[PDB]
Length: 408
Ligand code: HEM
Ligand SMILES: CC1(C)[C@H]2CC(=O)[C@]1(C)C[C@H]2O
Image 1 (cartoon, rainbow, N blue to C red):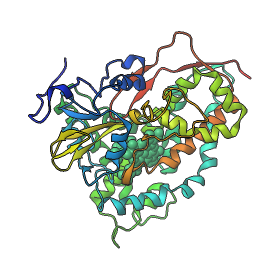
Image 2 (tube, rainbow, N blue to C red; image 1 turned 45 degrees about the vertical axis):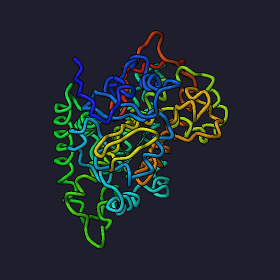
Image 3 (tube, protein in one colour; image 1 turned 90 degrees about the horizontal axis):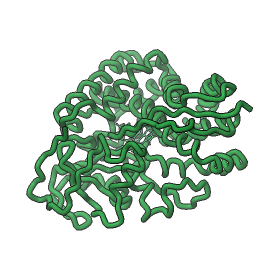
């Protein structure tokens, strides 16, 4: 049963589209394919859906890029749909606008900057190799449960100095954040609230122990960056450490599944990566253009007209980032991975002050994964007649990716 809200007076009927971000029409064919259905040659740049409490959707890459870059007009005070969930959302610095945002991003950058991430390469590689060698000789694996849900999680827990046995409970919380249970805005609001509270509960004792700590882990490093000459306050720290976990454990996991499904169906592309190691390294950004995973929102600051559309203060706009990288107006043949594409511009990591803090880590993890995968399993395919199961939400998800190959 579908829950609809009535459009407000300022929303004209010709802009209304029945789009359910948590259950996209056509989702069985793929998350990216389902979002692409929304982006027809003449659809308005901004459309409004009565689902998920009622909100706008930006349908073209230029709007998505622009909105991310304009925090003074499009605020981060709410970045989730439905509104109830977005209002319950308590993660730092992602809930913040400049200038409050900036010192917390600085703190994060102390741990996640490119020079720090480069130091992590060999530890990431070791984890990759270890997992891959578990099944490489076997000639088949279920890629989701045997690799994509394992690799980025072990990497991040190691980096964060946390026990790997916590993976399960943290993945469960993460999934209730990005796809909160419920068929109703109020239900989803509650689901998100309980998950966000679970993160705070888990993270509180760690914060208390690592304040002033001498650990070399990511949490200790970031926790102990001063904020305006003072220790980071408790409320902020809870939201900050929870966000680290949320970003580290869900994002790359999901991305890898979508990426691998495409690769398993395009051996010519795989062969190119295998024969030119530099095309692989240089081609990773094209993969990020092609396999966006995040669809989140911004809050309209003031009554305004934007791309010919009347917007009211408090309106939410969902930003399906796939609709930038896959916008046929930004990239010719957007659905094809072209490792040589010169222009790969995309919003897979968003734009503006919130542009992904973990993007260097995400690129390194993917780069190392492909290098170590192709070294040991150079050719592979999706099992015959296999059907991946897809989910849409704030972060896309996919499971059931049975791969097959001939042991080398
Ligand atoms: C496939 C991988 C990833 C994708 C597609 C991705 C996507 C994004 C997006 C779209 C945002 C902006 C959200 C918004 O403000 O509306 C973001 C922010 C952020 N991400 Fe990532 N992310 C990925 C990996 C990671 C990883 C591995 C981490 C490690 C902790 C991470 C940490 C963060 C943090 C801390 C922010 C907030 C930055 C700020 O508010 O200034 N992300 N990410
Ligand atoms: C949308 C995000 C991917 C981004 C902000 C969130 O809450 C995430 C789910 C984790 C972080 O990286």
